[PDB]
Image 1 (cartoon, helix red, strand yellow):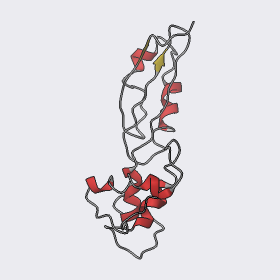
Image 2: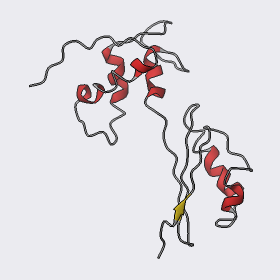
Image 3: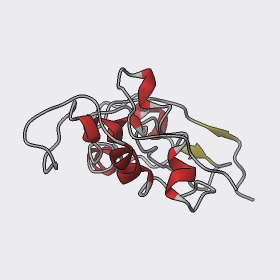
Length: 147
């Protein structure tokens, strides 16, 4: 049958896989493999860049289970433009804070995996009002054009 009778919900920081996870004693009754369940996290979550990535190990009826790591927020990429978080290889010399409409697009592009948008400007329209919540000044977005 294999049915999603239930699923585990937990949250942990990237790169913190330990032998004593929050589901350790709650997974031994399924896989019975701790190390084999941790090594799959230290190389999954850690592979991001300082951020929380909660996993949802789906527990089927009594056959097998699933697992997936949720990627970080778009903000993690916004810091690239200005230069707040760890970053390198920039167009400027050595300054951080405030960017242009070119930077926002530099990220929106790769951020078009599921986004139902083809135009970079059509997918950045939302990215321009995102970082604004953190504390950045959007510039380079004049009176757009729509038909």
